[PDB]
Amino acid sequence: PVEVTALYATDGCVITSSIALPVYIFSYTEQDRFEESRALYQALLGTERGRTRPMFVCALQDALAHGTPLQPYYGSAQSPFWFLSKFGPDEKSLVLTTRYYLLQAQRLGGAGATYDLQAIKDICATYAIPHAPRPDSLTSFAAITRFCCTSQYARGAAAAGFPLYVERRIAADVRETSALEKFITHDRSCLRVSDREFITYIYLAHFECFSPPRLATHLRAVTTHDPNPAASTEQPSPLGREAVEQFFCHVRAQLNIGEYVKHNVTPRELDLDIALKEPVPRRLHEALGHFRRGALAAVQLLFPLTMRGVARVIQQAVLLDRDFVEAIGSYVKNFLLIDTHSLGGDY
Amino acid sequence: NFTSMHGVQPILKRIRELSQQQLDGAQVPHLQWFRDVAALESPAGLPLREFPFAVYLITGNAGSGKSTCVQTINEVLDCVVTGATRIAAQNMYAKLSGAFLSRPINTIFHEFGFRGNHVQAQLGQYPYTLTSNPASLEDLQRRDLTYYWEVILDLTKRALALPAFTRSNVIVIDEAGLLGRHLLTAVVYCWWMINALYHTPQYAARLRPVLVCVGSPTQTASLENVLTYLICNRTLREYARLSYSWAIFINISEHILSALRDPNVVIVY
Image (tube, rainbow over all chains, first blue to last red):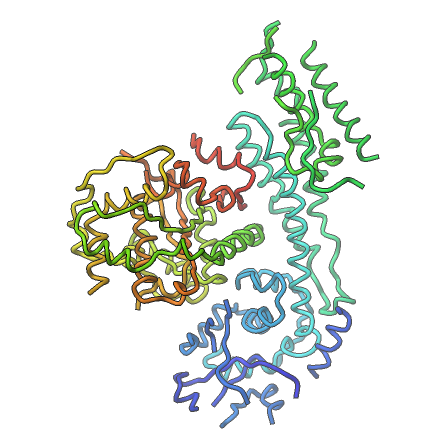
């Protein structure tokens, strides 16, 4: 037969004598992957981390439609209330999340192999596949086994497509947060602003950029309605677009070079350094043009050792512009562009 | 939880990287040194011996995700979760058992052998003076042992005449701000005790003890604890590579300002 894995269970006192030398089994490239995974279907907890370890190896198909016992570590004390509470009261969670977390995550690898159980439940919550009505509280492993083996979620397209949906959900979320955190690390590394203003900038960025409305919009855009990846109903998530275009306008305009000079600079009246990651494949001219714009704005503001002061102000004004950043900063390790009648003040 | 779920993954990556690094033969301590130390009574026979170790700091305001990060680390990585206090261990058990399975969590004191007769030990009895500056970590551990010498010596005496430190090498110490700085070295030393005394398979594997100190250094002020002694001391800042092994969970503190200024420490929202 095909190579499958099972999670042992028993109503009474799961121990070695019950293991003997009956069982209660309740958990039995892309296009091709879900095709074969559907073709498979029809219509003990312990760490070696490895969430489950096999006990032994060994008519069987009927045990997956009735949950009949098949007559001849740390999961020796499993409880039905345990499983019901820990894997949610929701049937879809109780089947899919259990199957993926205990069995599929390790055997299939990927990013989801490292996410904890609550992350898997959060992914499965927005796995809104249609709910086929169930014709028929759970008290023992027999009841939960009858509930899971006859479940619509333990057979066919849903069980075939859950792990791929997992991978795709982590991919989308990580890509969004990665772009936003790359910008955050950019503006973090070299911004030489006062302490309280730096702290409030970090707070406002990470909070208002990830306010509950944007998270709700992202989750709704990531909601699926068909287990088929080919027939996936996911929509383009606007989270990154909103976070970058819609709100850094306000932050950059408010927390700008004009206010910085007007407050933190007291006048009493320029060599570019590049840290290379990889060569840039028009970009250079655009970057120099935006550098020129930033320097010109700083010069206009400053003109209604002093060389160090003017270089520092030029560097700050060049950082505060977005065009120069999108032009060159994606390619540079660090952003100390400039090596450092009296421009004075605290620093 | 919506974004911490993704921000916490590099924390697990770095902890796994730390937990995997092996030590050279010249770096792993040998039981002959420890027996020689036991055979003496005064610190006069303690040379410039080094105890390699690694530390992972996780700081932040009051419960802004540090406990949940400990939960995720326990649920994914092989860590021996401990507590600074009895209440800390009870809180950690309450957090973990409500989600997944963790064995009964003991205090790090209970882990390394701290017992009742250890309470009455005269702490700070023998004198020490720093030799040079920046003080070599071999001198730092020497001083930490000297400050805590009675307890260390009684531990060694008991050890000569199943410890959980054989289980793994990543030890999660919650509320690490409540622990004295000297205890830090003791824990590492205590770790080696077990891994030297029982000839543990990690000893044959040349594995190094890794600490995951989770707490707020702001809540404790001297009238310098482990978190503060690691953030401030230049020697530990250099040896531990703390710039690349540090997490801050955020919802004057010049120290945490400099932490946020450092680009290479992870901050989780």
